[PDB]
Image (cartoon, coloured by chain):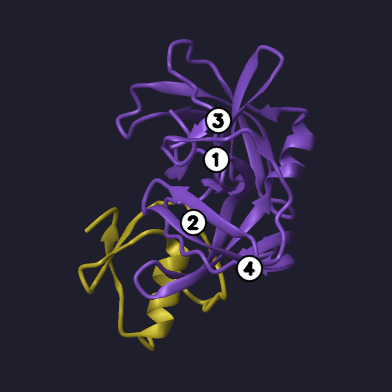
Chain colours: A yellow, B purple
Amino acid sequence: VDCSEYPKPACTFEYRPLCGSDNKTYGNKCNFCNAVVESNGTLTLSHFGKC
Amino acid sequence: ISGGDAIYSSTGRCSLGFNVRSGSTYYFLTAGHCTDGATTWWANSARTTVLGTTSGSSFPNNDYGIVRYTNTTIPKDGTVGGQDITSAANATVGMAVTRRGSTTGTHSGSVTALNATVNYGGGDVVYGMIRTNVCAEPGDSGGPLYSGTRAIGLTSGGSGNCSSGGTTFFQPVTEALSAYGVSVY
């Protein structure tokens, strides 16, 4: 996952989880990438799937 | 199984919008972004209970899809959780609505705008959407938006979350019904 085209003002809501370096499960890639932007690039991907 | 319940495809989990039928053929509606590229759907994460197979899918532009039931014994309730649905209606600004989804459950709010354009990026743009102040989170895609016993829309997407508040867009269900020649029951 590349969050380069983020942020996005809206995300669809299917669930395909990713596990962030903050130990939070992100519900989909769009949600994860908007969070990376919001953290100003400090959040990273820990692994695919739930945390 | 009824509106708002989890549905699983090969790729992830969405929510069932509404159970609908044409003649003697039963189907369920859900979001097009969930039906896109999915063939078979199941009722559980283990994929042991089959529901059926995708029969139509419209996304982007619109955001609806329909799955034809192949499972003969599963109960196909014409409700949303326990709520009965008896008809479909057009959304209006100011209308109180309720959404149900497989991740967040039931949340209420109101329609704040019609015919909105939502750009999910990469050329995925959807038009004609209902905007509301109801929250939603991943997994809630495709679930029903209803008002009383009236079917109004299918959850498509948005921002924010249920803890802090959000904005969610829904595909008008009337359009899907029409496209597929099916009706709620």
Give the image location of residue A4, x and y in percent: 51, 77
The disc numbered 1 marks a residue on which chain? B
Marks 2/4: CA–CA distance = 14 Å
Q: Secondary structure at mark 4?
A: loop
Which is nearer the N-term, disc 1 or disc 4?
A: 1
User: Which is more foreground, mark 1 or mark 3?
Assistant: 1
Q: Secondary structure at mark 1?
A: loop
Amino acid of disc 4:
Gly
B151 lies left or right of A48: right
Let me know if marks 3 and 4 both belong to one chain: yes
Q: Tell me if residue B58 comes above or below residue B86 in the rendering.
A: below
Q: Tell me if residue B83 comes above or below residue B121 in the rendering.
A: above
Q: Tell me if residue B21 comes above or below residue A21 in the rendering.
A: above
Find residue B168 and report its image quarter: bottom right
Give the image location of residue B67, x and y in percent: 59, 29
Marks 3/4: CA–CA distance = 24 Å
Say whether residue B118 is visible. yes
What residue does disc 2 label? A13
User: Which is more foreground, mark 2 or mark 1?
Assistant: 1
A24 lies left or right of B128: left
Find residue A21 and report its image quarter: bottom left
Q: Are marks 1 and 4 in contact (CB under 8 Å)?
A: no
What residue does disc 1 label? B17
Query: Which label was assigned to residue B121?
Result: 4
Let me know if marks 1 and 3 both belong to one chain: yes
* Residue located 64% across and 61% down the image: B95
Marks 1/3: CA–CA distance = 17 Å
What residue does disc 3 label? B39
